[PDB]
Amino acid sequence: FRNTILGYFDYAFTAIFTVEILLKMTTFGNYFNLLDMLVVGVSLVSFVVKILRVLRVLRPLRAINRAKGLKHVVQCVFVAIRTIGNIMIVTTLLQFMFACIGVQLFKGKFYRCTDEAKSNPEECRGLFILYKDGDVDSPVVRERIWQNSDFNFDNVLSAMMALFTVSTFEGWPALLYKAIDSNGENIGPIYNHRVEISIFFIIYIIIVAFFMMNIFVGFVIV
Amino acid sequence: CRAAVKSVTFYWLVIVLVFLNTLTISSEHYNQPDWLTQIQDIANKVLLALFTCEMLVKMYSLGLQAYFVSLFNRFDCFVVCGGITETILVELEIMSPLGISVFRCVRLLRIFKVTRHWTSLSNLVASLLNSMKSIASLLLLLFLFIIIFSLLGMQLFG
Amino acid sequence: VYFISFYMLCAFLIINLFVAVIMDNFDYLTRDWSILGPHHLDEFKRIW
Amino acid sequence: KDMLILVDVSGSVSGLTLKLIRTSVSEMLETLSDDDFVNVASFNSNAQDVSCFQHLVQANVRNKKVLKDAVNNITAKGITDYKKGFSFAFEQLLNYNVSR
Amino acid sequence: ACENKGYYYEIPSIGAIRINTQEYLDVLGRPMVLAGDKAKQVQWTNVYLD
Amino acid sequence: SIVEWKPFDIFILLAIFANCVALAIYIPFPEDDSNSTNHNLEKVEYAFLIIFTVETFLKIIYVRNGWNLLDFVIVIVGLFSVILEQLTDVKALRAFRVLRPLRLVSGVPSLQVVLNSIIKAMVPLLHIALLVLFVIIIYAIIG
Amino acid sequence: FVSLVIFGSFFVLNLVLGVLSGEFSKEREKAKARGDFQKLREKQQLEE
Amino acid sequence: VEMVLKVIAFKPKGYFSDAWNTFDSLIVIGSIIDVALSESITFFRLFRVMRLVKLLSRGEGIRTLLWTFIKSFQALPYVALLIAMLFFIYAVIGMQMFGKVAMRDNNQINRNNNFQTFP
Amino acid sequence: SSSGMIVCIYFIILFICGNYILLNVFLAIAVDNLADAESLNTAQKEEA
Ligand SMILES: *[C@@H]1O[C@H](CO)[C@@H](O[C@@H]2O[C@H](CO)[C@@H](O)[C@H](O)[C@H]2NC(C)=O)[C@H](O)[C@H]1NC(C)=O
Ligand SMILES: [Ca+2]
């Protein structure tokens, strides 16, 4: 019912904007003008439809040209964006090399079975007995699945996304301890196999997350 | 042959070879088809041969003692020598399964050859290279700060 | 792409506001209380 | 079989890896019958029996219950001494005073 | 383990307790199979519920 | 009339690093467990404390300087800890030995001035820290 | 909690970053009179 | 007692000139009405700690540091409008796309974290 | 309970004195080395 009620509000609201867009065209005959005709145009055409329902989120951006302060603040953003475009090309190129190195290092080593007793896809089949919370008196039957990690280094894109998540400092200890246990190409992990592989993550964090991000803020300040 | 080096048709041709070098490194993936590794490792030898020929051209054309002044040429010849080292190493009786993947990193550095002429990037690089005695001094103090608290944690929560 | 673009744009806009605000206070952030400043003038006004 | 279970109760086995040892001994005692003689001992810089038996027992339902109860009541503390632990175990298999 | 004719086992989790604590009977059965037909004797267990 | 200049001025500085290295290979086993490496490291710590004690009488000629005050404290506390440990939370009192790597900062003036320049930039942040303390107190009371 | 994060973290981090960036500028303008930039300028000018 | 002593000493017409005294009225009136209801009830009892900043902020090393930043946040009010616009646009866009995802308890889209409502 | 809650001051001093040094080691480099890049650029734009 709320959608139906709000559906009548747009009916009236869209009339006004059609009146003003034709009213100005009477006395005229900028790229900022096409957007105003587009916002009312998407509400008209809508009268698939899912894309047109999302594309009509441009309504709050129609006030940019009707506010001097808002227009000036918006222009300053694109002025600053082009200035910070030199350090963006460097921190993106540097992330790609680390993504390639991570692809070389852990390319398909982040696999594991549902139960930590089978260490290859052949044995990781069928059902297994799972013991809840460590109790040996509460077993439950579960199916074992040989599944990959959510953030893996299979290709250059998954590696780039995982490195982005690491550089955002979120969930990176999990990936670090998952990469330390990375045993082989298509076999399960071993507890603390190669601790010394943490040097990759430490160097990446120091070079990009700490240095390349602070240089960005410093450059903006200067 | 300096007319074929200080020209515009050679610098813009080296960029294509560098890009094709990056393309063969940023194409490996888990369970990659058997026909892709063949292209990868033939392009390996072919493009390495082109790069070492390019180094031989840019090694005896202006001056051997004036090239060592430039850090890039000494840095790039190191990569060229490392690359020519592993071609026979892999084909010979030195398998090094972990040594195959580690060097590809040391051979994928040839991507810095597209950033030599910036004049907006090297201007701050030359400034941060002059303050290396302070950059490596702040880091060595941060490392000492991390070491002391790690040793202290090893006692309290060891 | 939704989450990556949001996390990039929001961080950039937040630091843009931070530095924009800091720019307006370089008079106070580099006041150099030792030599002079409006605080001395305020003290003089209160004493006068 | 004349089994004799040696359990490491030193300091380093404290935590999860002791709960696994106590469960492993309990499941191991279930593979023994009335013809099998067993005893459980623990060592941490000093080897001693974990129960009141002090030698091999017939490992029937009555005796296995006592050993299982005592195994589920051990604690981890001290240093590791394999020389003293194995000498104690080798001495109990040379008894021949009792039925084996 | 094998300096004294034994065998070595890994028990990293609870799921490996059930299987690894019964495999010691394979080693103990080596002298029985090498005996030959002198070890083929019928034995009867204790009374137990089926 | 002991004299010090450059003969051992690098020797004691390298001994500090050697003791820092010996403090990094000590594995803190749980529930009072140990191995052979820790057994040897205890005797090595004895010798390391001997050198530090032997270098507190020659540097007594100093007693008021902060760096020397800490240097003397991290020696007297170690001696007291050894004495009271031999005549027995005693094992938690040897946590003063982690300040020995911090002693290395005073031996290198080039790296010593950097730390001074870092502490000297903390006075302006005291107002912000004081504001944060009041915000924390107000929100804790409101909660 | 929302007002605590905005005031406790975002407001304070702006204060810390601004005040710290005001000391760096204060220590840079004072070190400019010494001639630290001059030494860098003359060495960079004597290379091309 | 302090308030009734200050009002009869500072000419109430002029007593409301100061911003500190006017904001101190609410706590005093708030604290004087909660005592009668000790035997909707915490609105005034909660602001009993607000009197702290009324006198523990008189040091002109921390008050000026605040004032120079609050007076600068309102000097640039259109910059935060960009953040508000970005939040609105992204929340609305996420509402159509991820608004139909089910609400479970062990997932990250749960009763407390979801796209179902604009807040 | 007990007196084991007082050991939380180890993870507070470490987080406070650690995130403060990181702003004096990675931000003090970008506002003292890059702040020169502009200077250099500006100085190289007037001598060219
Ligand atoms: C029973 O065990 C004991 C000790 O394990 C064996 O040793 C003898 O014990 C008896 C009585 O205690 C005494 O003769 C001596 O104290 C021990 N030594 C010798 C040389 O006899 C003993 O041999 C075992 N068997 C019997 C029948 O006692
Ligand atoms: Ca042990």
Image (tube, coloured by chain):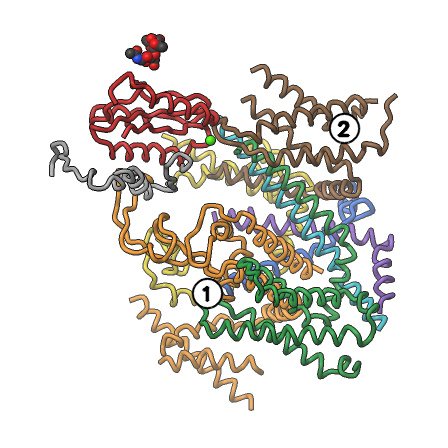
Quarter holding residue H23: top right
Q: Which chain is yellow?
A: H
User: Which quadrant of the structure image shows residue B154?
Assistant: top right
Indicate the amino acid at tag 2: Asn
Task: Name the residue beneath numbered marker 1.
Answer: B30
Q: What residue is rendered at 67% in x and 46% in y?
A: H65
Chain letter, colour blue in render: C
Give coordinates of residue D95: x percent, y percent: 32, 19
Image-based side of D76 in relation to D22, left or right? right
- Which residue is at the far bottom? A29
Q: Which chain is green?
A: B
Residue H100 at x, y percent in the picture: 33, 64
Residue B107 location, x and y as percent? Answer: 62, 65
Q: Colour of chain A?
A: orange
Q: Residue at x 47, y 75 (%)?
A: B35
Q: Could you say which chain is coloured purple in the image?
A: G
> Does B32 sit left or right of A77 as displayed?
left
Q: In the picture, which quadrant includes the C terminus of chain H?
A: bottom left
Q: Chain of mark 2?
A: F
Which chain is rendered brown in the image? F
- Front one among H26 and A27: A27
In this picture, is I21 found above or below B152? below
Residue shown at 73% from the left, 33% from the top: F15
Give the quadrant of the N terminus of chain H: top right
Which element is circle 1 on? loop
- Disc number placed over residue F137 in the picture, else none: none
Q: Is residue B59 left or right of residue A169?
A: right
Using the numbered discs, state the Cα–Cα distance from disc 1 to disc 2 in whole angstroms. Answer: 59 Å
Determine if the C-beta at disc 2 is less than 8 A from ligand 2: no
Colour used to depict chain D in the structure image:
red
* Shade of chain I as shown in the rendered figure: cyan
Residue placed under numbered mark 2 in the picture: F68
